[PDB]
Structure formats: structure tokens, C-alpha cells
Amino acid sequence: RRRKLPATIILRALNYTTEQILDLFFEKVIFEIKLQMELVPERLRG
Amino acid sequence: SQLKLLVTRGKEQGYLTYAEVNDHLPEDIVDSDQIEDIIQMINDMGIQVMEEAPDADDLMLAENTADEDAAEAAAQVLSSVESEIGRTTDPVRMYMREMGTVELLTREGEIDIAKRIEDGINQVQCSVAEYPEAITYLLEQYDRVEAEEARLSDLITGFVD
Amino acid sequence: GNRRIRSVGEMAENQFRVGLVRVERAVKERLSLGDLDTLMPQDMINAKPI
Amino acid sequence: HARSTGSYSLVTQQPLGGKAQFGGQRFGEMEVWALEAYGAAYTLQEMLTVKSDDVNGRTKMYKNIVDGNHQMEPGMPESFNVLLKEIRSLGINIELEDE
Amino acid sequence: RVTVQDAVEKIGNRFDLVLVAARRARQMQVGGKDPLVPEENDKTTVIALREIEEGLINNQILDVRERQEQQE
Amino acid sequence: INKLNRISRQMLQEMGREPTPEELAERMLMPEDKIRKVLKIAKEPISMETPIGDDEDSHLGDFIEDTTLELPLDSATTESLRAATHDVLAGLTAREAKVLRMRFGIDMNTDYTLEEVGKQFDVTRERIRQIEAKALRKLRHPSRSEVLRSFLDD
Amino acid sequence: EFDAIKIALASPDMIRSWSFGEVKKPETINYRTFKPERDGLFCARIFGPVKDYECLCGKYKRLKHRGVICEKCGVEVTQTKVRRERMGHIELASPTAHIWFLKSLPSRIGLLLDMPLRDIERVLYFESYVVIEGGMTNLERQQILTEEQYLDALEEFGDEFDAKMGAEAIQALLKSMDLEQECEQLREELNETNSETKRKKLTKRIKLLEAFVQSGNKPEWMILTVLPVLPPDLRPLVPLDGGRFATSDLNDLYRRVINRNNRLKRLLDLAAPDIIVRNEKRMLQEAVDALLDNGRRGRAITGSNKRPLKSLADMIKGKQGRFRQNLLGKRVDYSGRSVITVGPYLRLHQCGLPKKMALELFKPFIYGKLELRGLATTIKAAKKMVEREEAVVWDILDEVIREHPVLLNRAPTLHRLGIQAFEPVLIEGKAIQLHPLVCAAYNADFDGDQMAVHVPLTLEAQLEARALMMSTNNILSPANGEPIIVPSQDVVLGLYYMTRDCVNAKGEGMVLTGPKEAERLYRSGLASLHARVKVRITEYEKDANGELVAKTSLKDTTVGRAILWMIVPKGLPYSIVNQALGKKAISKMLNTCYRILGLKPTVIFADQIMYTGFAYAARSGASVGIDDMVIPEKKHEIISEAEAEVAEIQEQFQSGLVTAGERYNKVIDIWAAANDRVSKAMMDNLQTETVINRDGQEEKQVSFNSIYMMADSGARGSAAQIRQLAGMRGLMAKPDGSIIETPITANFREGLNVLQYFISTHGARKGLADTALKTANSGYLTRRLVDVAQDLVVTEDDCGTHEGIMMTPVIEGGDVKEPLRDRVLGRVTAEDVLKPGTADILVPRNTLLHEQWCDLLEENSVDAVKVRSVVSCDTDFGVCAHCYGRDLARGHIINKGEAIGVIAAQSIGEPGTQLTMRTFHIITGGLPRVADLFEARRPKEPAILAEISGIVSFGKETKGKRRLVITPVDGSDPYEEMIPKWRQLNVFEGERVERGDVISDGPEAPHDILRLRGVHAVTRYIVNEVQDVYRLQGVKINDKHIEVIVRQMLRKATIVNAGSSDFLEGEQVEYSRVKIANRELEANGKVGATYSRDLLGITKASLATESFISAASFQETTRVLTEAAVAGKRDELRGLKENVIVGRLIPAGTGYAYHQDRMRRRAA
Amino acid sequence: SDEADEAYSVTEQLTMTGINRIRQKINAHGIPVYLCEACGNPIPEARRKIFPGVTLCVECQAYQERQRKHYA
Ligand SMILES: [Mg+2]
Ligand SMILES: [Zn+2]
Ligand SMILES: [Zn+2]
Ligand SMILES: [Zn+2]
């Protein structure tokens, strides 16, 4: 019940980096090359 | 600004949880006495620092008092409290502070202080003993002792013998 | 599923553990001083604060 | 439970509370508003003075009632006397002016 | 006595009526007097209120009788 | 008291349940009455603001009564007896009435004594004693003291 | 005897003037003998003897030794109630700043020294020296120096330099202070400090300086040097059982002060160093602080417990304090409670008192009777007689009780009808027997409630009960003049069953000779109670100057209609009983009887109605069976159709045709609609039945079903509970307010299975949990309102003002929801009401609009009458009887004296208890909305008004808000507004708008309505809103009561032009004062000061009371008392709450004459 | 009062206010819009026959329902 810190401060305190955090919490929409997009059709629900 | 934001956000919200106060109170403060005084003043404001959010009806029903001279006094205390950090209210903390200001003694130092007290009292001894009516009245005391108006050990505790 | 029940057994066991920590204080300190022989496990534990 | 006149509490000289103490009835704030909403100025003055807290007027009321003279000389409640002394025991000097 | 409407009408106030009846009933009870109305084994309260009904009693009459008493 | 606590804290453990005061006075050297009064010495009495509680949020002080009051029935009886004594002394001669009012303490702040009474009657306290006795015997009669009899409580 | 209370700061010398001796030792009693000590807090020399007329040790044991001071213990022989009166004092070895004048928010010491609070606290707890008149040496008066700094500044300055630290420093700062001189310098700066914060605080400080001058206080008295000691019997150390003692917390705090003060004297005598003596002084400071107000320092010192000790400030404040529940709420003698029962034979003026309660309460009266009649020789003999309960104590009880009312009171006294005087009728048993028609006033059912009876003791209180509170005087609700004697459930069912015809009963179409013959026919059983007969009825109509002409005719009525006509008094028409007579029919019957005939015939009529209702309801034989819940046969058809509809909607949802929440809404709607069809079908099955007949053919008449007869007579129940009994139960809520979409297709004539009985539990427990907590704070609105409207009293007969609000109908879009005759009845007209011909004065003026004038008004169709309002009364410190109206608790006009403010508070609070406890939004409702209304809070989205009149014009574009200016047709336009473009406007820049008109849309803040338009505008706004709520739930409460509460609301004025008067400009003043002030100043050759009327929410207006004994009740006692002390205020009592506290008559009721005569004396 | 009769009134108000809120959200009588106000798509015939007066197709409706589920 102390002062509020950013939640990912503790994910860094557990010895993660930003690439690892974003690997944990997100999915990587991968674009390739022009300017082509790999597609997971389920993503674009609308 | 920070605690000012807290005060204004409370006064528009009508309440304050402990969490919001913790987020808004400064970070220099380490003790809980300044924090509880801040909570007391801010409740006097008054905004009624709570633990949980009040119900919608508890805002309408809760009587609001009491502006606004105490409002100004409370705000002028809270705007200044954030600056001085060492502020304290316990007499025990003040005592421990002003006692820690002194530096401890050592064994030979205690010998020095004892001998210096002995020198001071000895100088007092000599100054008094250079007063003749002093020894006259002392002989009179011992005489009225010898008349058994006192004890041969009561008037004085013997000599340096 | 978030709330569980205590009863006499568990509440009384908790109180007895509180008494036991109070005992541990005195027993540690008394085994700190002297530890001399003829000191037995009857003089170190008085039943009142448990 | 009922009571004409019985036991009286030590610090605050009111009739005791409860049936085990043979106590009186709590005439509270809302009953006082109800009495003020009528005109019962005397009803209230005696519920607050003679039937409750005025140690010297309760005995005179009793003597009068057995004398068959229904009149009260109410004096002043012991609750207000204790209040005056307790304000005076702070640094405030509170007092009752010339009549 | 059930409703005091006539006693109230004679005096034209509901607190002053209480006061007039109370002082006349105190005269009739403690100070000692004779009911101006035939008391049918009523307390001094009801006697005073009934008297105020018949017009026999009011504040003017009572102060006038106090004057006459002094002239005694 | 510290010694009593020490010896009890030891004896209860070594002896079983608890030391009865005879057992403490035996283990100690005290006379077992001193021990009992030491036990009876009260301890740190209480805040009279203590809750009772939850019935009305009335602290403890509400139930401690004032036992020094003359209850209004008692004062009524007192003043009734006062008026009755007056109306009885009315049925006495002036000498008897004065000597009984003054020998007792009625309507004066005493409690006069026999020599000081007989000063005002010029008696050397013997005739004054006799006059008091005669008045008391006269008031002793029934049909003169039936009310005063009723004032007796038994 | 005093006529006024004064207050001030107590001088050290005056604190020794009170004292009877200086307490020195900390001890209390002996621990062995328990005797008081020689200088302890419980002394005998200081605080007097322990037994009456008997010194401490015991040398002097006679009352003849009175007043003499013993020699061996010095204890003067007096009464030991003297020990409850005598103060002592404590000679402080160091000055100790009084915590109220330091740690209070403005900090009178701080704002008086013109010094910051932290700086004084640094000088006080021995942080930093302060310069106290440091000569010419470049030293700054009140300039803090620190320790090292004080040393080095003393370096090079062997000269005085006059610097001190500690409470002595503040005492030498205050003592040296010149108050008038600082007032002079502050006036001279206020001359030329014409900037807001500077001259603002200049004036705000010169106010307190001038006040400290006037009050006689010296500035340095706020630094205690002597400390008074509460007397021993106000803080006892009494023994409990078994050597046990119980003390006050005050003794602990006092001992702490005495110990530390004695140790400080020791330290000073022992020449200890600076650290030790400083720390001892800090300790004494904290001890004295905790003694006065424990908790303002932190932390509250705890006793032999975890909880703080209670202190003086605690001994006064808090609900455990003196003001809360020892100055108003007191335990009372000659009183007692029991359990109430019915006693349906009594009259409206009596109550069955048990013989045992009656013999206990009336004890002194009985003793007096036995010794008066000679049945008991002395009071002891009478005591023994009535203790044995002999045979003549009972005759004496009958005689004593004969005309001697008893007040019956039930616990939640929401209004003044929770107290009524009844004549005792002695009964056996131990239950109080309470009249049936009085339960509505008392809110009392006979399932175990209890009542408290009190006994009026004086002739004046006997006449106040008889004349004023007797149960046959109070029959109209004081909130609205409708009679409060409406018969409830067996009565109305009796009158409904008897007054309710059927098509073919015994003896149809006989022509009776009259009601006597109809009753003789029914009681011999020749005719049935509802058998339509021609009956000859003689009704008497006062159609005259009160003449009562008789008229006989031949009506068509049932036999019960005519049997009941025998009880109705003369003036009432015959159509009053010729219909079914449900519940409202009976209430309207009593009401028309009251409007025609008055109070005596109405009381008689009410009793006869109760008697006949109970009698013919018992003869009704109206039981309740299981076959009386006629479940309709078309219930399972309707449920099959609804189930098919939900199955179809679920099939469509499964096919993606709808969403999830959409289909939820659809199915909730389907189930609500099928529930409506089932309820309608069952009530149409239940509300009619077939019957035969004169000629022989079946004929439909209203059903004599018993459950329906009870729901339809209004006696008890309604078609919703009927629906739950035989129709289906429906959809059920959750505590959140969501609706479980699995309905209860069962009823209670059938059963619920385990799942439906579980589902119903949700809403059931929610409702009960709310009703259990609403019961806790049942009377908070009433209390809040009586805080502000308490001192308002009807003090004048006519103010003469011609101001008055224009009462008109409320047309809620369609028709009227409240006509003009209802809103205007009882009010005094302010001007002449002209006929629609516009030349005929219909009702002239000052005409109490009773039902005759009101009918005349509705007849001519005059639909806007200017009536006098309590809010527009020109009276000072009160209201007149004309601007108020009639009483509504008594049919007549208000009396001079009546305390209408408390009546208004209770008349708004008690009816509010029938409103929802939580606000619901549809126009919100519930009690919390009403409380927020009276608190006059600002709505967040204020529809902005037009502050000045003139041509509309805009300005700069989007400085946050779009800017506008209004510029008069001929005047200046210094007012412009930062209108938010979010506030989407309503009028173009090319339409000249009048002043006080809408710019944006949304809720109108009442402050702006009041400031733009008349006070009448704000008052009409407030009454229309709050009555919107009260009509939302169906509750009726008059507008007079809201109007008086509002007049208590807008009772402050703000002065614009101070004129030739003596008022500061930006100041708020009691408007009733500034009115008389400008009136007087305009009387002489001056001109008055013009002000802007204000408005305060009730919790804000009640905080501004002219007195301080009253204001220390419902406020913070500490701030109010500190302010009154530094102001030297005096309370010339002149109030209700203050005279309650101080123990004399209030100026409201019968006390009005006492206060008038007393004001005569005080002005002579 | 009985303490369950007032509870009955509370429960009645609670259920009725809930029922009528969820009824008002239906808006059965309406306008034939024929095309989505979010994506302009053809609101299919069956959805306009079920709910006369829709403004969103089922996709945009369910989308909006998610957001209004959380809040804001
Ligand atoms: Mg009940
Ligand atoms: Zn003595
Ligand atoms: Zn007026
Ligand atoms: Zn769409």
C-alpha cells in the first residue's frame, strides 16, 4: 500500500529487459521486405 | 505542486483514499509522524482521508465542514511542510537528537572530568576558608556540639584522617 | 471460494502459538545467561503467560 | 418497568439506567424536538430539570407533590453545572452575568 | 374534558389558554379558592378549563380579581 | 508484592495448580493475614469510561450509583418528622418545651448542655435533668405520641 | 437569574481566584485507609469534606460545628457536595502554551503574533531562540535565531540582545505586544495597501486585533501559568466491589502534569544542565496538552489499556460528551415502559395503564392522598400501605389518576405525534393498551413494540398535556392537514364489507322506513347486509349561514349503507356512505366531516367508525383460505407462449442474428411481458364472480373473494402481492440491480422449488439489509434540518409586507399534477384577487384562504393567486402569523409563539422516511437527493445564465472557452464570460437577451438563480424540485415547510455598497441585522447600504448561529469555544437549544410569555 | 411495519427499476434505417425484423458491447 511504481519496474527487478518483456506480453506482428505484411487472419477481426 | 495537486484533487473528489495520499505525499519523508500530521491537516481541510472509496450516497449525505479560515491555515501549513524534512513532534526524538549531538567520554576523560570537579570544589574550599568568620562560626558549631547541642559526628563527618 | 472457516481448534491453536513465542523469548534469554547446571526445564517456563 | 423516584447516578446525578437498576426512561433529543413542536415549555423544563438532573429541585418537587402543591421551582441542571466547571477547568472563564 | 376547542375560542390562543388555566387552577388548588363553576369531582385543571369555557375566567378577569383582593 | 509474585510464580509451577494463601504464608515467612491483605490490595483500578458495552454505548460510569443522597422519600419523612416534633412540643408547657428544644438541638445550632441550660433556668443541672425527664415522660404517653410512634421504623 | 452567559480568557490571577488551594502532591487516597491525601488531587482542605458536616480525621462531628475549620487536618466541616464545586489550581513551574490557542487551525497565538505556526512551535519545543525586543542592534523582532546562530550573534554583542526560547519566549512576545498600536499601523497600511492579498490579510488581521481589544482579554493569557483543577466529584475515584476502584482518565492526566511539574521544580532547584531542563519543560508541555486536549499533538497517550485517555475537550465534545447526551438526552424519573396491546374499546383520549405501573409512577401523589384523607397517619404509614397494596390504595389510585394525562412515546420520535397525552384507564396485566387509530401516528404495530409513559408533574404540564398534546387535539398531520386518524385494516374491511352490495341477497327491494328499520331487519336476520333496498333518509345540510336545514328523501342503498348512516353526524351528505367505502373513501369521509363540522364531531365520528368497523368485520367472518388464491387457467398457456418466444430468440442468437446482451434484453422483456399477462389474467379472474338473480339469469358482480376483498377494500394488500400469491412471481433482481433472467414461473399457492427459492433470496436479503440500515440513521434529515430551523419562531401577528409568491398549478407537461386550490389552501393572500371580469375583488387581502375561499377561487377559475410566503416576511428574528399561514396541525391560523421551524424540520423529515433510502434515477429520487437539494450543492454542469441584460455578443475564439460579452442597450458591458464551447449555446450572437436568462443548458445552480432573479425565484425552484421528489414517491408535504427551511437557508447578506452605514464591503452579515441597520441609517439623515443576497446549504447556514452555547452543540465544541473566548462573546440566551441546555423555558411554546415579561423587565 | 414489509418495498423498487431499464434499452418502435451507422453495411433483414429500429449490425453492436462492458 506504498507509493505507486510502474508495473514493469518489477519485471526489470526480476532481471528482464524490454525485448523480453514485450516477448512475454505481446504478439509480434512481423512485417517483411515492398513493405509486405505477414498475416494471421484471426487478428484482423475488425 | 504535488501535495497541492493532491489537495485540489481531494477537494474536487470530496474524499481521499490512503493510496492516493501515499502517491501524492512527498518521498523525502521517512517517519510516520509527519505523514500523520499531513493526514490530520488534510482531513481538517477537510477532505476525510479514507481507506476505501465512499459510496455515491455517502458523498451527498456526508456533511461538509468547515470552510474556510481553517482551509487557508491548513493549506499554508501543507504548502510549507514539504520543504523542511527534519521536522518532528515527539519529545523523545528531539531528546535523542540533542543528546546524540554530544560526543561520548572515555576512561581517562572521566578521570580528567572528576579531577576538574575536584579542582573546582577545592578552589571553592580555599576561597571560603580564606573567610575568617567562616572558621569562627565553625568553631562555634563545634563548641555548641561540645555542649551536646549536636553530635561530635553530626556537625561534621570527621576530618581527612 | 475466497473465504475459509476457522473453528475452536484453529483459533485456539493460534493463541497457543502466540503463547509459545512469548515463551521462546524468555527461554532464549535465560539460556543466554549462565546456562549453569542445576538449572532445569521447570524454572525457565512459568505457565502464566502461555 | 416503571419508576417514580429511585436511584441516582454518582457522577452525573441522573436517574439510573435500566430495569435492574430500577432506572428511568431516556428522554432524548428527538423527544425534546417533539416537545418543542408543541408548546410544552413546562413539560420540557421539568423533564430536563426536576425529573432528571436538578438535584435540589427534584427533592422539592417530591415534597410538594406529597404536599398536594403541583408547582416546581426548577433551579438549574447538574449537567450544566458540570459543564461550566469543566469549561472553567480549561483555560476558559465562563460565567453567568447579573440577572 | 376531551377537546378544549371552546376554551381556546374564548381566549383566542393555545399557549395563553394553558397559562390562564394553569394560574387559575393554582389559585383553586393551592392558594385556595372556590370554583366559579360546579365541579363534578374534577381536578383543578378541568375545572379551570371549563370555567374558561363559560367566560367566567380569563386573564383580564383574573388580574381584576387580584386588584379586588388587594383592595381587601 | 514483587516477592509475593516471585514466590507464587515459582510455587504454582513446582506445586501443581496454584498456591493457596496458606501455602504462600507457609512458604514465605509471613503471618498469613499480612499475605491476605497484600493480596487484597487493589491494582490499577479502571477507566470509568470503559465500555459496558454495545447496548447503548454507555461507559461504565453510568451504572455506579450515588449512595450519599437522601432520597426524596427520605427527605419527605425527615421534614414530616420535623413538623410532627414541633406540633408535639406545642402540647408541652413553656419550661418543658424550651428545655426539650434546647437540651436536644431543635431550631438552634446545638446541643446545649445541662449546666448551660440550667444557667438560663438557674438550676444546678439536677432540676434541669428532672424537667427534661418529666417532659420526656409526658410525651411518652399514648394519645400524645401516636404519630411520633408511627415515625418509629421497625 | 443570569439572563446571559459571558465567556473570556481566564487570567492566572483569576484562576487563583477560583481556586481553594494549590494541589502539590500527585497522590489520590491512602491505599490502606482510603482517606484523601493532604495535597493530592482528592484533598479535604482544597476540595472540602468527605462526609457531611464532619471533618477528615473526625475531631468535629457535629452540624453545630458548621463552617468552622478543623485544626488537626484543616478540613472545614461543611456538606460534601461542596467537594463537587471547588476548584484547585496547579502552580506551573514553567509557562505552557494553551493547546487550543496554538494547535487550532487559525492559531490565535500565531495569527495574533503575525507569526507562522511552525515557527512558534519551533520556539516552543525549544528548537530556536526568538528575538524579543532586541534593542536597536539590527535584530528583528520575532526573527528566529538558531542555537549556534544565537551564540555567534551573542558574540560581539555582550549587550542585552534580548533573545529567548520556549513558552516564556511566546509569553514575552505577547506581553510586550501593543494591540491598539498594531491596529493603528494596520489601519495606516490598509490605507495604502490596495492589493488583494496584502490589504485582504491586513483587514483580516485588524479584525482580530480590534476584537482582542474589545473582549478585555490580554494577549498573554493564552500562555498558562496557573492550571485549574477540576473538583474531585467531577472525576471520582470510587470503589467498586471487592476492594476494586474505578477512576476517571482525568486523574491520570492530572497526575502526569503534577509529577512532571514537581520534577521540573526539582530540576531547577538542583541546577541541572540545559538539555535536562529543556527536556523536562517539553515533557510538561506535552503533559498539559494531553490533559487539556489529548490527541492534538500525537499521539493520544493511552492508559492501562490500548485506548487513549479521555480529557477535558473529550469530556465536553463527542456523543459521549456533555452536550450530546447529557445536556439534552437525559434519564427521567416518574416514567416507565411496557409492551403495548390493542385495547380496542378505549376512546381516542385514553390509554390502558397497568395498575402496577400506575401505582409506581403516581407514588408521591398517592402518598399525599393517603395522608390528606387520614388513611395514613404519616408518609411512612402511607408508604407501608401502598407497599402492602391494601384496599384503599386502589380507590386512591382511581381518584388520583382521574384527570391526569400520561405521555405515551415510542422510540423513533420522527415527529411530534410520537408523543401524546392520554388519560389513563387502569387495567389489569402489565401491557399498555394503545388505541387503534393512534398507531399511524406512533408507527406502532402490536407485534411486540414497547411504549414509554411519562407523568406530567406540574399543573402547567398537566394543562400542556390536556390543552396541547392530548390525542383528541392532534388528528391532522402537521406536514399536511389531512387527518391522521384514518382507520387501518379491520376497520376498513368492516366498512367495506357492510357498504358493498350484491345482486340478490335476502330482502331485495324492500322499502325500509329508515336506518333504524334496516338495522332491526338485519339483526333479526330477515335481510342481508348488502341487499339493495329503497330507504328513507333524512340528511341535514348546513346550506345557509350555518342553519342546518333538514331534507328527507328515498335513496337506493344497501342495508349496510343505511345501518352505517346511523353513525354519521348531521352536516354530512348521504353520498358519503352510498358507495363501497374502501380506504380512501373513509379517509375522505373523516376529512369532509372535519371541514364541515370541526373537531368534536370528528373525534366522535372516528370512534364510532372504529367501533362499527370492528363489529361488522367480526360479523363479516372474513377468513382466508387456500381456495381463495384462484390461479388463472390461462397461466400455463401464457407461459408456453413466452417460453416459445425465448427459445426462438435463443435460436436466432445462436445463428449470429443478435448479440449476447441484445438477446438478454429481449428475453428479460419477454418475461416481463408474460408476467404482465399472467397478472392481468389472474386479476380479471379474481375481481368478478357470477351470481343469480331476481329473474333467474346469471349476472356478473364484483367478487366477494376474501383475498381480493382485502386487496380491493384498501384494507391490506394490493394486486402486486396478489400476483405473487396466485399469478407468477416474475423476474428477480440481484443486489447489484441486475435482473436474473430465469423467472419464477411459480406462485405461493403453488410452491417454489429449491432453485427458485434460492433465486428469490437475493432480492430478499438485499431489501432486508437495506431496511435494517435505514433503520439505523432513520432520523438524520430531521436532525440536520432542526439544526438550522430551530431558533425560528412565530413571533409577530402581521408584518405588513406586500411581497408574496404567485401560487399557481403545476402542469407537468400534460395535465396538472397538483391544482391551485391544493397549493394555496391555508395561505394568506398578499393582494386583491380580481374576478376574471378584472374588476371584482374576489378575495380582498389577508384573507385566510379556507375551503370556502378556496372553492370560490376555483369556481371563478382564478388560477394565479399571490400568497404571502415565510421567505418574504419582513419580520426580524422571527416570522409573523400572516406570512406563515394556517397551522395544518390545527385547522385555525398559527398562534403567535408557535415554534414553526422545528415543526418544519420534522414535517420534512418524518415524511421523508417513507421515501427510498437510496437515490434511484429514472429525475432522481430518494432521500439522499432531498438532502443534497437542501445542501444547495453546485451541480457540476451548470446551465449558464445571462448575468447582465443587453445585446448578445461574442469575443475571442477558444481560449479554452469561447468568450462572450453582453452589452446593455445603453449601459456598460464590463461582464464577459468564458463560455465553454462544450457548453453548446442556445442563442445566436444576434438576439439581444434579457438579464437572467439561459446561455447553455443543464442543471441550474440555485446560487445563480437567486443572484439573477428574485428570492422568489430561488424559493420556487427549491420547493418545486424537492416536491418533485416527494411526489415521485407519492408523499404529500406542504410547501410552507420547505419555504421556512429555505428562509433559514438564505439568511446571509453580502454588502456591495456600504453606504453611510458601518459595514465593511466584502463582508457577509446576518441579513436580519443589515436590514434593520440600513433601515435605521435611512431613518436618520443617511442612506442605507445595498447588499447582494446570499444562499447557504443547511449544514453551512446552521454553522452560523448568533449564540455559542447552542453552536457548541452541533459543531466542533473546540473551535467554537476558542473563537468565543478570544472574542469575549456573550450569549444573551434568546434561543431554543440554549435555554434547553441551561435549563429554563424555551421561548417557543408556553415560554413565549415568560420571555416577553422578562424582556419587559430587562428593558425597564 | 414488521421490518419485512419495508424490505418488500425496497425489493419491489429494485426489481422494477431494473426491469424497466432493461426494457427501455429495447426501443422496439423505430425507424427503418436499413444500413449500419458504423460501417454502412446492410443490416440483414432478419435483424431489422427482430429489432425494428436497429442502428448497428451485429458485429458493431457486439464490439460496442465489449467496450461498454468495461466502461467509458
Ligand atoms: Mg413492531
Ligand atoms: Zn480534623
Ligand atoms: Zn410577515
Ligand atoms: Zn455494421
Image (cartoon, coloured by chain):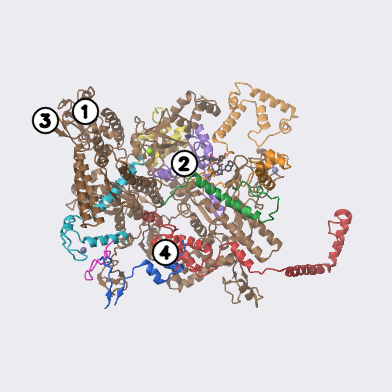
Chain colours: A blue, B red, C green, D purple, E yellow, F orange, G brown, H cyan
Q: Which residue is mark 3?
A: G697
| SS label for mark 1 | loop
Residue type indicated by callout 3: Gln
Residue type indicated by callout 2: Arg
Above or below, comparing residue G401 to residue G997 in the picture? above
10 Å crowding of disc 3: few (<14), some (14-19), many (20+): few
Q: Which mark is residue D26?
A: 2
Residue occupying the point 61% across, 29% down: F85
Dividing the picture into quarters, in which one does residue A44 lie? bottom left
Precedes in sequence: disc 1 or disc 3? 1
10 Å crowding of disc 1: few (<14), some (14-19), many (20+): many
Q: Position of residue G1060 (x, y in %)?
A: 40, 66
Residue occupying the point 27% across, 27% down: G619
Q: Position of residue G697 (x, y in %)?
A: 11, 30
Q: Which residue is mark 4?
A: G1063
Q: Which residue is mark 1?
A: G529
Above or below, comparing residue G442 to residue G391 in the picture? below
Residue occupying the point 64% across, 42% down: G50
